[PDB]
Image (cartoon, rainbow, N blue to C red):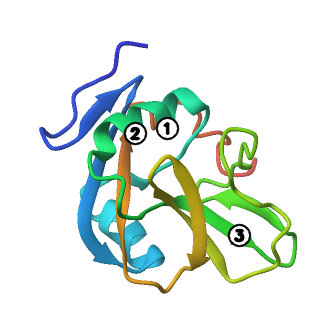
Amino acid sequence: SAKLECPQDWLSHRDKCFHVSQVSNTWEEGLVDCDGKGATLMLIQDQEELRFLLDSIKEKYNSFWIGLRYTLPDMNWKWINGSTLNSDVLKITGDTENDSCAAISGDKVTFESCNSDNRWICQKELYHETLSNYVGYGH
């Protein structure tokens, strides 16, 4: 769609706005930082998303956490919203079996122990009221 309004620091792209925080935190901690604004830790759908990231990244020679968590036991990458990773866009090894959480580092995506001091990317999705689903359960 045409995107709704988001705070000025947040780079606006197809219905989502990004804050490329050049300050470091741990993965879960950066996630909480996104929670703090009423936003989410970056949820990537397609490579169009990341290509705009590469524009907004600016530095590249850093690493910025996105909402990619490696869920074990399962061995798939899931997002914080509960979606499945599109590993086909860039280098994100699915079968790694490590304590990994992923971060943008340059034109690549890298992954390491979620506890590493790294910067992060918050996205505030302009469409967060898209599908809430359920009326609870059905009582």
The one of 62 and 102 positioned closer to us in this rendering: 62
Q: How many marks?
A: 3
To which quarter of the image does residue 114 belong?
A: bottom right
Residue type, label 1: Leu
Within 10 Å of the Cα at label 3, are there few (<14), some (14-19), or many (20+) other Cα atoms? Answer: many
Q: Residue at x 72, y 42 (%)?
A: 86
Q: Which mark is residue 70?
A: 3
Pick out the residue farthest to the left.
Answer: 8
Q: Which mark is residue 50?
A: 1
Pick out the residue farthest to the top.
Answer: 2
In primary-sequence order, the first of circles 3 and 1 is 1
In primary-sequence order, the first of circles 2 and 3 is 2
Q: CA distance from mark 3 to mark 1?
A: 19 Å
Q: Label 2 near label 1: C-beta < 8 Å?
A: yes
The one of 51 and 83 positioned closer to us in this rendering: 51
Q: CA distance from mark 2 to mark 3?
A: 22 Å
Q: Residue 69 placed where, x, y %?
A: 63, 67
Give left or right: position of 52 versus 131: left
Residue type, label 3: Tyr
